[PDB]
Amino acid sequence: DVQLVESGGGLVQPGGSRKLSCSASGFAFSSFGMHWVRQAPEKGLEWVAYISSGSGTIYYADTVKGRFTISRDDPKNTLFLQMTSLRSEDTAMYYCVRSIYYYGSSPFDFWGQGTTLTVSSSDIVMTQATSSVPVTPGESVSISCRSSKSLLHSNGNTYLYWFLQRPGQSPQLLIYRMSNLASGVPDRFSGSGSGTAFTLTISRLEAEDVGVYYCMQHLEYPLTFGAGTKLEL
Amino acid sequence: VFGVLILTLLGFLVAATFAWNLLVLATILRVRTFHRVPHNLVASMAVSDVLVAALVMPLSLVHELSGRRWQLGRRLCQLWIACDVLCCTASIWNVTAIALDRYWSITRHMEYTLRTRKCVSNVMIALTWALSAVISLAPLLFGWGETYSEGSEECQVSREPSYAVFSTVGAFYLPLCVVLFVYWKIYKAAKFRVGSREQKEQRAALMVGILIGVFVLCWIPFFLTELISPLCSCDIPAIWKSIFLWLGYSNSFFNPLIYTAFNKNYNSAFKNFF
Amino acid sequence: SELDQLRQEAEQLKNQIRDARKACADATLSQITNNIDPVGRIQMRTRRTLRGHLAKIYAMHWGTDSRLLVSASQDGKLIIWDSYTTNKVHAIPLRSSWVMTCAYAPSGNYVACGGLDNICSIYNLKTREGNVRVSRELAGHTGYLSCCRFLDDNQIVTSSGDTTCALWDIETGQQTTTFTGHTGDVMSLSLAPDTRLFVSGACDASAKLWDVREGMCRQTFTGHESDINAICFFPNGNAFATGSDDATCRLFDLRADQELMTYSHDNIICGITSVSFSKSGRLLLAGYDDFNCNVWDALKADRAGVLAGHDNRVSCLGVTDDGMAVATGSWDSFLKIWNG
Amino acid sequence: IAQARKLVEQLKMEANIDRIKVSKAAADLMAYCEAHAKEDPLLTPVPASENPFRE
Amino acid sequence: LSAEDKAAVERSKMIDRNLREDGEKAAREVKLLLLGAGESGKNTIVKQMKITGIVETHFTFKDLHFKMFDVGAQRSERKKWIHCFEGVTAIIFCVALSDYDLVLAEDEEMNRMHASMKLFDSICNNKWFTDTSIILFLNKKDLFEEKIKKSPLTICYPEYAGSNTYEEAAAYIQCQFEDLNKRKDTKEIYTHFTCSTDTKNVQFVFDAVTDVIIKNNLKDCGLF
Ligand SMILES: NCCc1c[nH]c2ccc(C(N)=O)cc12
């Protein structure tokens, strides 16, 4: 019974100060690292920050470091994000994501509802070949994307993730490491790839399957998100 | 000297005090059950006892082999007369350290837990080596005494009337008093914990007496002579001083004869080793 | 009255069985393998060493993917290792610290353990939350547990010191079938590759072959002198090897129902703790009480090598599914992984 | 007194099985060991190129 | 190594840090093994010092944490699990004085006071408990006083050769249980006559444990 509650938001003048709050319940909060992901209007997702269990590792984005900080409260099961030195380019809705890392774990499984934030007015790159692909009902279509750097490691494990976002709904994890299906997802979806080119295959498309797909990489920080593909009937 | 027999005996002493300490140091690391609190002090004892045998005793042997004239200039005299007053003091304070542990584990077994123990142990293994350095590099890195002899090359530890008393008091007399007091207390406790057959009473006294006598007879004549000679402005023959020096150096031979040979686990490990 | 003639009939039946057993014995297996090229020399070195148990180690079990491992110690802890990187994945605390067995589910979702509390506990490793929790406690034995094996995700078979073995149903927690016939404590189990029969060694110096579906004894094998401590199945599925306290290991054959060969020496006087085979069945590894582990040629009874790296006695021993490594546990609280 | 009857019944049930010669079974073990010999990493050492436990 | 193995290493570091932290909490405790025979008075002993398989009990007296394991409900072979308990601080033994006149139920030619002696002889001289002390309790003494006036001790041992009084019989009984120890150079036996007494039962155990700990500390120097 995982539930996510967030507090804070609303219009504010540039340079204002506030704090973003998160609430967790129904699971061991002390054993999960947390991520902050924002999505500007008419834009894709963007990784913001990461904190591990025990507060032993903290990371920030290139355009975020210096004007942001993260923290957690184990006894109260609370997550914080202090707001300072705000700009007009930070108008986005912030999500909360949990992740656990051991041999065989599936990170980014559960996503929060998020809260709206708005104000008054190299590295691996993920590229999707086609912005919008028409869909024929009852047929099978595929979505393909590529990367500038190979995602194949010495240990043999590759780091590619697929996320589906329903219209007006929080995204959910479909496939992790390009070949493993997440729990609670029907067997219609199937992931594939070879070295640098990855294609996602769907056996059949239904009325529920319509949505926006995203691609992710986890070889190194920061985490880059490819532009979403609009599935149109 | 008085025949080649003395030289052969000194060489055998060098070889024995090097090889035995090397064997002990190898054994502590080889055996993986030797990772407890009272075993780190034995490792410090062994390394301090081997650092003098390996590189402080042959230098004295060649220095006294023919004439009281140093082979090199000021490049070696200062270095040789350094570990001599550092790798020996760190051995006297290691014996005092092993004693204070046994006392606090028989007199106060309650507060001496599995943490307090390790903490106080490691703290002592530091202060011991720190103080050693302070005294050794005092008549040099602050300006004091000679430690420069002359063209006659008479390499000798400073003979300043204040440095002699300071170093002797800070190196020997305080550890001597501490060891005597703690072992008297331990012996009384062991006597009391027997009465309320006879081997358990006639072996404890023998062990304590062996420890005290071995520690005392090998260092008490040297230190008292040093303090008495400069201050009382009295000159002693150069033979007695040399003999006392060899006694002080030879104490390192007896030093692992007690804390390692008579133990059970260490003896079993030695027997297991070829 | 009728007791005397019943005893006489039982004795004559036993004599008839032994007469048939002797009559069907044509020749020993040693003569057949006289002209077989021997293995030669076997050398193995410690590739990994795992530490973290602050007590004696009593059991272990390999995962079905030949990478994960489970160990149980009398410190009250259940640790899941990653053998490749010597990492720790889970650490489960037990209600009772007197544990003497552990097992790993073939599917990889469940882990079971038991001990002196006469209760077998089953743990769930894939909960929705990021933690493990007890899913079912099985009770009904009147003695300490000795072995534990998973038939599948919903069945399990245990053996205890009350001279009985039982087959459980995890969903309901009720004993489906019980096995009787042993007159002493049962100390070991071994499931057939087909998962249709199993064998058990007891303290009365005997072994029996059971039928899981019918719940009846089919065959019994004797020949040991003191007590049986370990048992294991041949990869073919038609033979098994045992290990005792008389410092001897013996190989039995189901189809002929006899004993084929014995593995004894003259410098060995301590009992065997564990027994395991190789992937092809050419070697037989047996742990010993003198801190050593030996390797025997299964078809010639010749010591091919020695695995001496432990301070205290060896208590557990296992071989991976693909046959690339062998792990050993001991009372010095260290797990070592060997390779050839 | 039922223990004696149960024991004698079990003994009677176990004496009706069929048995084969030892040499056959020995040949069957030797043949299996020879057939599965090439895939035994412990028996035949493998090069360190594909050894997962690469220290 | 690849942004997903460092997390595994830090998780393992947290795991073994927690393991080490929990390990030293259970090292500052005294473990005692409770033994006996039948209804010799283990229940009364537990009642005097209190807070299926193995039963455990916890109690504190003077900032010492005690754990007592009762293993009287096994009925299996003692040989196959007695080596699990090697390393306990001490062993508590309970004997009923008022058992010389009584015999076993299923067997008539067996004194109930001889089986206890056999069990004590077996437990005391074991390859696993060579350096472990034993605390001996003689439980029922008032009923022994009541029955000693009319019945003689010669029924059990026809060699008592003494007046049927309390002291001369109790001392003989205590002696009969103390020469069964053939390891006098390494083992010590503490005896206590108690019967529905007060905190005296716990104070004796505290004193014996303190003595055992002090002697164990002294033996590490080769000085005892
Ligand atoms: N060869 C040992 C000499 C030594 C060790 N510690 C000392 C401390 C003081 C003095 C001294 N010459 O005053 C000498 C020594």
Image (spheres, coloured by chain):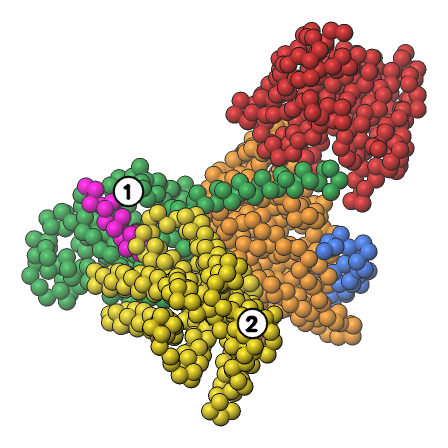
Q: Which chain is yellow?
A: B
Q: Amino acid at mark 1?
A: Lys
Q: Quadrant of residue E50?
A: top left
Q: Which chain is green?
A: E
Q: Which chain is orange?
A: C
Q: Is residue E195 visible?
A: yes
| Residue pictured at 53% horizontal, 43% vertical | E19
Residue underneath mark 2: B77
Please tell me the numbered disc located at residue E62: 1
| Residue pictured at 44% horizontal, 77% vertical | B245
In the image, the segment drawn in magenta is: E198-214
Label 2 Cα crowd, 10 Å radius (few <14 / some 14-19 / many 20+): many
- State left or right for residue A87 relative to residue E131: right
Is residue B260 magenta-colored?
no
Does label 1 point to a residue whose CB lies under 8 Å from ligand 1?
A: no
Q: Chain of mark 2?
A: B
Q: Which chain is red?
A: A
Q: Is the residue under label 1 in contact with that under label 2 (CB below 8 Å)?
A: no
Is residue E209 magenta-colored?
yes
Q: Quadrant of residue C15?
A: bottom right
